[PDB]
Length: 182
Length: 13
Ligand SMILES: COc1ccc2c(O[C@H]3C[C@H]4C(=O)N(C)CCCC/C=C\[C@@H]5C[C@@]5(C(=O)NS(=O)(=O)C5(C)CC5)NC(=O)N4C3)cc(-c3nc(C(C)C)cs3)nc2c1F
Ligand SMILES: [Zn+2]
Image: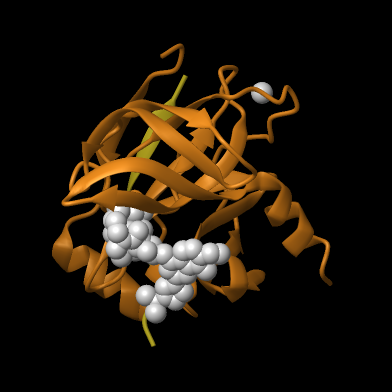
């Protein structure tokens, strides 16, 4: 990898629940990827062009606890398992890849950067197959090109007997397509 | 009902 990553837990369980109910998060926000949670489950969200994008199957309809109360979904594209909120101030946004590379890097929930070989528009095979548990909880995590630019957000995996052989992701082009629907 | 909450972050470089 030419890219590295590290994680920082900013909230605990009790404070999490609380903030979920009020919808008011005054904690300072940093970084390009946020670790995100509802009461039941947890997953990632990625920032691209000022919008925080995550998966619909983790956050469905829900708002995002923000510094001035809850934030409504700007974008909701059930068809592509994609939702988006306006990035809380402080969230450093990634920008889309323009180079067309096939040498991708998926950044996971535990801050692993793992090589992915670009296969289609929304598809890429893992160079070293991992266990599924190694990947679970990373939906809404970013796929990056070698220069650290965004090509897509992690949606799903293809696997057999608990070992992940390939990854599906929403292409960054579909995010701008969703943003092209006023 | 409830909101999604930011319980952490991943920094890149
Ligand atoms: C445009 O085409 C697609 C493609 C896939 C879609 C889709 O895929 C699922 C399939 C399932 C799957 O692959 N397996 C179970 C097997 C391997 C597991 C691979 C490991 C990690 C995977 C990334 C990951 C994940 O981390 N999920 S998560 O973070 O844990 C979460 C549950 C908290 C959100 N996602 C993941 O595992 N899966 C996503 C789901 C949904 C929707 N789901 C719902 C509700 C009702 C559940 C509404 S729409 N739409 C999808 C869709 F429109
Ligand atoms: Zn690029």
